[PDB]
Image 1 (cartoon, rainbow over the protein chains, first blue to last red):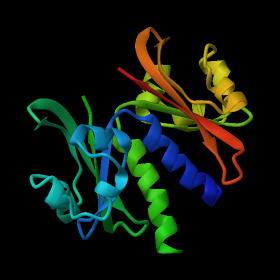
Image 2 (spheres, chains in turn purple, yellow):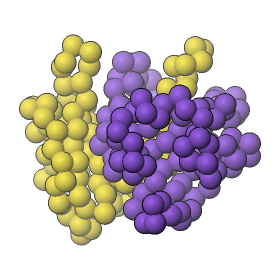
Image 3 (cartoon, helix red, strand yellow):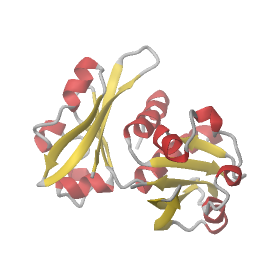
Image 4 (spheres, rainbow over the protein chains, first blue to last red):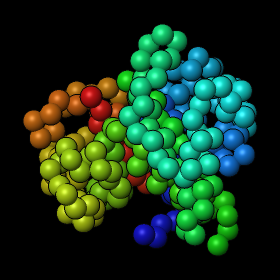
Length: 110
Length: 110
């Protein structure tokens, strides 16, 4: 439904900050477009500039995000090992109004 | 139809969908502005229209979200019971460019 653009921006930033799942998103090119602090902590990075704009496969060479770009098919409850500990990922494609795949997002939860 | 604003909208919607923490947000008046499916399950609703636009205190009478609106001060790792489930809540204020508190979001996690 309709909302102010400034608000939409601030809502996104607030959600990223408040959650304790990690988020990593990419564009269709595979460059990281979105990351939260929880994700930086899980992955072992100091701050968002260490990661934004990087090809995701450079940092997570086994990522299935580029695959979700290709299929446009969500993947749920995938257990992964991260530095020996276990996390669970969901991977969702990001579509425009016209149905086209413009990106993809992974969560990483405990 | 600017591409980037459309993307920002879809990013917010994607995060809301992918996460498995509950999210509940309010405006300054205390009415619920955003809720996800995990949060609907905790509150005992099937249909978002039973929740959106409701005063948060009508559904979570012990909520401190209205208090965060007042203070503009974030609150972290607060243990609560919601419909008999034990959860941990973070509460983050939403501010505009002018510093004013325009809303607040809670996350509910295991």
